[PDB]
Amino acid sequence: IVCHTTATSPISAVTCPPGENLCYRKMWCDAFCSSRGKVVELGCAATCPSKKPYEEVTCCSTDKCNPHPKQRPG
Image (tube, rainbow, N blue to C red; front, side):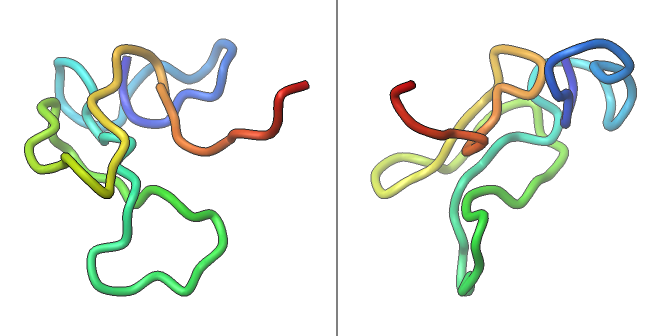
């Protein structure tokens, strides 16, 4: 229940202090992108404070939660 998991076993461990979220999966850009993947910087938070219209991913309920791996109806 931390920053970057990835599905399985070694991960879900130690990155930032205790609680929810930690490094939020917050989408976006701020001033500049011109980039491809496309989606997400990172922080140390446990809250979700800004975030309404255009707009961002959230507070994690879970290990990763996550953007944008994201494929097709398959």
